[PDB]
Length: 163
Ligand SMILES: Nc1nc2ccc(F)cc2s1
Ligand SMILES: [Cl-]
Ligand SMILES: [Cl-]
Image (cartoon, rainbow, N blue to C red; front, side, top):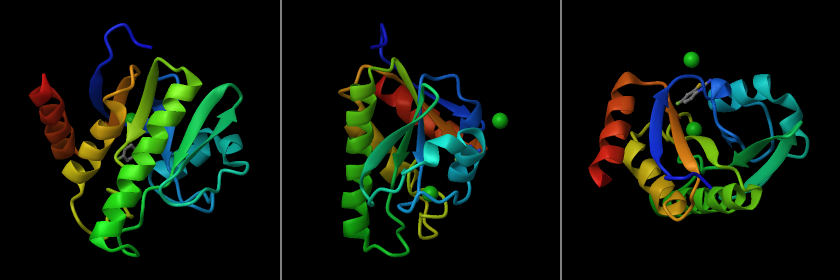
């Protein structure tokens, strides 16, 4: 793992990450989708061979030797707040298992269920806290990707708060 495991946040295209593997905010059917999922499809299209997986799970497919971890957050349009929250926590726990199995020293990760799966709500804090619960016990350097200038500030603050 990383010598001093850390969290960082960058405001850029996750398709341009400088990490040893990437987490896709995937749909359950392995379709190209939109947002992060569309950029991942354009950069690593080979990774979508048999990528379909249920909500609350993660499935890794290699693009050459570069791992793409397809993590399926819930669509809060379809789920109750209670069941959506349980599936969102589960998806990040499956990501932590896959990152550990792969033996990577770093991972690029988006906030799951915060874009077109958010059901039109701000889920920054909900999704980030589930990311921390899952990844805190791993020793990989985690680099969180966002697009919004205000989200970059709010994620940076939440990382710095814990030290
Ligand atoms: N290509 C893209 N990368 C990201 C990374 C984070 C994000 F929130 C949106 C996008 S769209
Ligand atoms: Cl960029
Ligand atoms: Cl999303």
